[PDB]
Amino acid sequence: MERINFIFGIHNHQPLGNFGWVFEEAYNRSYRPFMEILEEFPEMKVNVHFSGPLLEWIEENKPDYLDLLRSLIKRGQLEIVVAGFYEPVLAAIPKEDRLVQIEMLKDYARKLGYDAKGVWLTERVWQPELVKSLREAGIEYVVVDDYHFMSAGLSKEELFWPYYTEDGGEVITVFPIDEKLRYLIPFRPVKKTIEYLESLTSDDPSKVAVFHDDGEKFGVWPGTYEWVYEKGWLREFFDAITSNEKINLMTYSEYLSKFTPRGLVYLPIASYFEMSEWSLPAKQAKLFVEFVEQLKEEGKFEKYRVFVRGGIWKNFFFKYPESNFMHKRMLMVSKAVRDNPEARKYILKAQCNDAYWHGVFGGIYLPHLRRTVWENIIKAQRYLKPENKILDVDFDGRAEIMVENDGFIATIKPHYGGSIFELSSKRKAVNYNDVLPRRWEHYHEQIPEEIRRELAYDWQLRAILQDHFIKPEETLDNYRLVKYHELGDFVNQPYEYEMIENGVKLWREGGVYAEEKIPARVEKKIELTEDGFIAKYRVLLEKPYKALFGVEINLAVHSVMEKPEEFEAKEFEVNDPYGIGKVRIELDKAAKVWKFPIKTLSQSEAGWDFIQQGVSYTMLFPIEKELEFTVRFREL
Ligand SMILES: [Ca+2]
């Protein structure tokens, strides 16, 4: 009967902030061999997308590769597919930024000798209004998953054709990635794809099956290089796929030049299926996984998958407050910097998606990806005149206080212990509080014993200047892990405040609960200094009681494999060369200092990830009725 049309595509992306060797390995393990083997089969057509940073790393290091890509473009073997230059999730960035981001990559594709008409949707996060944006960028089609169509209401059998979708009276074509093909290519034996595709043929000559996935699958992921190249899966596939008379190879643009989309369809906010799991808060994700697994155990997943639903990507901002804070801070700067091309480039770089969420790849859990985002938010903001302001930054209904001078930007949350949640250095372009609290992930609970004994989950968010109250006999380990007895209620409770020149005055009428409620009061005077900040404390208990007042300061120390340690100190220094650099904490009175790394257990593509997201430093001072001291943070 009719031949089945087949579209083959890959997506190559490397996030800003990745280690140098990671790009190098991805190139020698996948980007290069894949294209070298592609050149051996003149009839093979591939639809490829390269993220901007990747193309820049390649220009600087592997120039010859680009001539190879130009050559393959010229012989009709490659269609260049674009997206936002720095791989941002389009739906999560200002519409104005979407245009500039896409146009930057279209300019690059143009330099390779191709007029890009298609967009690879980053993390396939779809929102109806993206039609307007893509259309203004001159994009005629976007790639999405078959799952998006199933969520709209269509069955898999009507997903072997692209469709139109509209919004604002504007339309754009949409191609669905066949989930089956993602399963088959390239990990299942070659003949399995040939068999699956041959079975799709019909009397409709426009029918088409689409495969589009991570290029990293062809060499980078563990065990794939041996499978794809050493054992020859790719050469065997290119040979079979270009010989089969029932399978017609073509690029997206080629398909559209010969067949018109099947019809009109509307899509919901969705992503590829796997994202439904991760984008859910921990507790629900576990349930979701249970449901999905219990559907396969009862062999009824296939006929009922079209009705399974989970979370949406944007809710990572709910799951991870730190990501939300980071995101809203960048939206804030993007707007204020929109008219300054130089400053704006930094904010566009900050929109690289990877550090804002967590699925299987570390993402937000990788400190180096996170500091890169902050680094860029800070550099973009440094162009603005410093100004103090009170406003709800992360939209939780409780205004933040932003104090700033020529060298720093501090964000205080009165509602949460009157602590500093952001201490950004304009000189180092780092956020000293670029840390993450320890949380349970639905995939926890197999974890080895060594890591198990070090696992602990926080109940407190982690910031700078968090006021504690503990028993004199309390131990570090108890505190290190989350066992210790917290006597005060000032860590996660609101404080009143008063604005003062160069700072803020906060105080809280709380209490010290032990055997009875001993009402207490905490007063803290925080002022910005040219090299950090100074905080003057005054703790007062209504009635005598022997305890230890503690001021905790969390820091994004990342290159200092620190370990539990306690010592007496009036002043101490921290040296984190690859992280926050050098800083010094000065007290006007010796204190007991407890120090411990904030350890997180994370899921990755290559085993567990037990990462130090920072180090907690908490100065203890004995108190019975009255207490007074000063803590000064100094940037060196
Ligand atoms: Ca708020």
Image: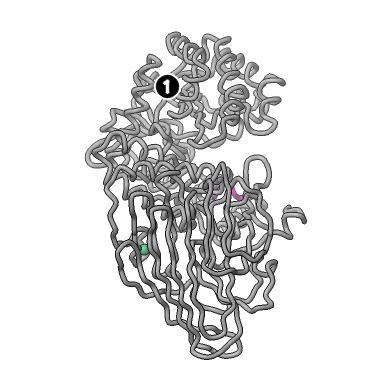
- Within the image, what quadrant is residue 593 found in? bottom right
Q: From the viewer's perspective, is residue 208 above or below residue 583?
A: above
Residue 62 at x, y = what percent?
52, 17
Identify the residue shown where x is 49% and y is 61%.
463
Taking the image in four quarters, ligand 1 sits in the one at bottom left
Left or right of 130, for residue 87:
right
Q: How is the image coloured?
A: one colour
Residue 461 at x, y = what percent?
51, 64
- Within the image, what quadrant is residue 617 found in? bottom right
Query: Is label 1 within 8 A of ligand 1 (CB to nearest ligand atom)?
Result: no
Identify the residue shown where x is 63% and y is 20%.
234
Residue 453 at x, y = what percent?
74, 60
Q: Is residue 487 magenta?
A: no
The residue labelled by disc 1 is 80
Residue 400 at x, y = what percent?
35, 63
Q: Residue furthest left?
A: 169
**Amino acid type at mark 1:** Ile
- State which region is magenta: 300-304
- In this view, the residue in front, 55 or 426, is 426
